[PDB]
Image (cartoon, rainbow, N blue to C red; front, side, top):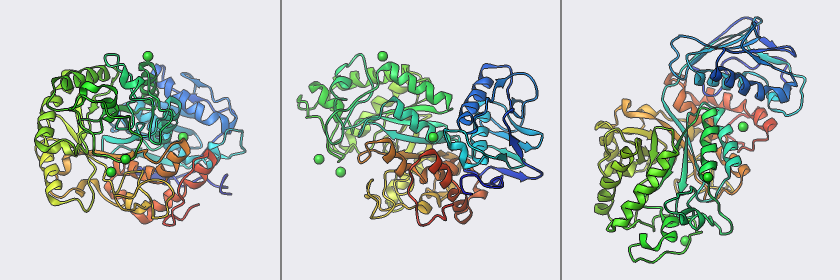
Length: 499
Ligand SMILES: [Cl-]
Ligand SMILES: [Cl-]
Ligand SMILES: [Cl-]
Ligand SMILES: [Cl-]
């Protein structure tokens, strides 16, 4: 009865593990007449409609969303110790009630509810159910405020609809930030009016050659809007001064030798660099960041700074000293890969650490020192949360430069004590980056994203006290029938006792 269990799934069997789970009494059962009661506000109804849309196909129920009556499923905004993202979920014969201070909390409560319901809820045609929700109470709040997933649309381009699909994948686990790697050596994916060729030429191809692609301003705004409706703050990234071949290949003048390199379709890194000794370079950067910031309602702007191996140390430091201020100039907070920690991060900046267990002490110290100086840390170790890394030597897709990363390794660590000497309070959260040198379609993205994606979300959300591989793998194993019913391909790791 994998698809439709006789009894409801345990109240604590959800990912991320809830802060507090108190099971008790009989469960709630959704029946044909169940109404979704929300507050009389736009944001409230919005979450109600989102929930109704998720349940209608599989249940075949009307599930009307209204601001009157005593609906069996109630989403209510009220005071409480839940912060901006927490919530309380009460379930019993009298109905299911999700309480929170803000819509995001209600949205998160919904993500938990869809896991309490049976796997059949993932189907697109009416199913028998039963639509049971274990009885009891759940009180849940996040451990970290930065819980993101990155999608590389530069190596291989993915259109608006494919991005919306990935957004839906991550929304399941309460991620609250979507980092978009909009430019690299193989492509420039965002239209910049002041520099037209970046998109028309720099976005004309991708890894492996052939058609590339890019988002017009309108398409990008639609991605931001859709992400916002899924409570994901979009963090755009324009990598610099390295990983800039797409831009350099579009405008000869940006190159040190004034010659435009060919468009790049390979899968290597570290060979490109903006010309630090040219003034036009900083006019370019200012134009790009200014236009990007205007399309960014979010608080952050990622300027990369990784693998600038064709940029001498002194030039890198000089380049960053000059460009970081451009971000604040356009009202945003700067974010960069941890290489930025070696180039004096400006006040309020955050750095994304992608080091590994084997990384040298000097490099780790430089990052820990930045944390000591007030720089926020986003943890995404290459040998832990890089979703493009192979599970084993036999994985058909992905890379292996950071070694192999099975499910347990990806999950089995604590962000608070991860980086030696780094102040725990400097850790803002975690991120799961999905690079695409080897991925060209949505299904390949799923196979490499799952089943590690949920684990990273837990590290960012759940209390350290709930962290435990032996019990976590049981909760992960339970997702199998849900992913199968949803058509989500995933690596069936031998470390997980799949249900
Ligand atoms: Cl999905
Ligand atoms: Cl447009
Ligand atoms: Cl190459
Ligand atoms: Cl390389």
